[PDB]
Amino acid sequence: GAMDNVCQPTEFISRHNIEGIFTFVDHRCVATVGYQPQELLGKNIVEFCHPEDQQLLRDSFQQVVKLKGQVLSVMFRFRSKNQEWLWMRTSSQTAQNPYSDEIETIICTNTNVKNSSQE
């Protein structure tokens, strides 16, 4: 997988509903998880998330939505376009507008990241 949308990732801001269905995905997502924003949009964020970790992912969304605004931080394995468990940290918090009723989740790549276009 060698796209040419952006330079390198770090974290991509993807909005979604409580379910995790991406109501928005920042174009960094292609450099981050290979999946273009549209390749994520309408998709359940956790569907990519490792099963055993989806419970934690959804949990976060359940907390941000419960506390309406309060940000959540959860690390999960995002099966990216490379078909690899991309460990990420989510910054889930009720989106701004008009997706206020949604949840702005900033998926940031973990592990070592300096001059690598992956993670």
Image: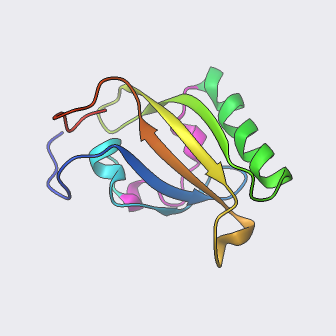
Image: 79 above or below 33? above
Look at the image and say whether residue 43 sits in the magenta stretch: yes
Which residue is depicted at the point 16% across and 35% down?
115
Over which residues does the magenta segment extend? 37-50
Report which quarter residue 42 is drawn in: bottom right
Which residue is depicted at the point 16% across and 50% down?
3
Which residue is depicted at the point 72% across and 46% down?
61
Residue 5, image x and y in percent? Answer: 19, 59
Image: 85 above or below 88? above
Residue 66, image x and y in percent? Answer: 85, 51
Residue 7, image x and y in percent? Answer: 17, 52
**Residue in the foreground of this view, choosing between 42 and 65:** 65
**For residue 95, side relative to residue 22 (left or right):** right
Residue most extreme to the bottom: 98
**For residue 62, side relative to residue 11 (left or right):** right
**Residue in the foreground of this view, choosing between 94 and 25:** 94
Which residue is depicted at the point 63% across and 37% down?
73
Look at the image and say whether residue 40 sits in the magenta stretch: yes
**Residue in the foreground of this view, choosing between 71 and 9:** 71
Image: 98 above or below 53? below
Residue 100, image x and y in percent? Answer: 70, 70
